[PDB]
Image 1 (tube, rainbow, N blue to C red):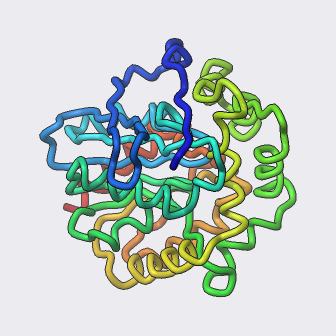
Image 2 (image 1 turned 120 degrees about the horizontal axis):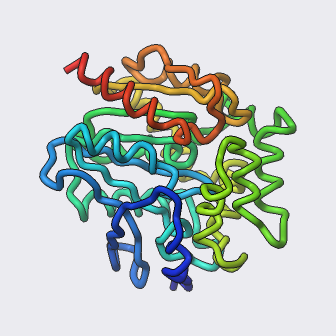
Length: 310
């Protein structure tokens, strides 16, 4: 039962533009011996809470340009690091990382912190998992900010959410290749390739959580879960579609990183139609898969859109 390692704290000593204080949650229900890190910024007694979920192969550092904007508006911001990433503990075996392992962690976190009036902010795996959370406790969610993401349902139900896996060759195929094949995986080099506008310092922050390959089991497993979806993931993701289509009635805002070869327009437009009340997406021309790197714009416009619909 859950053999995991912890990244030395010194590895985070020289981060670029990450002045956010660490918060930890030990022994969450179903996760004994595991410490999870999360940021808790802005007014702790705020009525609105922005739950920012990251994806592969990043961490809360990805939301560093969005957190200040949300906090300045008077809202509380919660940005957790999934187990295997950021400052959270990292199981050594890939077999321990599953769809429900990460999903149940999010549910436990929300219950432990008793988060309400949540504006769900998602992208990539933050969305694959995040988008399935509201149907479990709908009264806790108020709004949604969705950036490049979708649902991991089966190919028949939604072909658009499976088609990108095989084409184009330089899309998810190259992405997965870059992550699961290198014996010595260098995340600073990976991120510089998939987010060409990052500075050397910023790319370095993405390598910070991983002193060596033994810390990368979660990183290697994520891409494999997009290609091989277990029955639980398919069932949960399918039920989630019905939620956004028939049950959801909250404020929504969508932003698409137009240069993303994985989850761009091909996926985002079909996603827009499935989310009841999702407005016309904000298309960010220069943004790639990691839309949050152009997040100040997304954050500001989302707040403006929300204010005009209360």
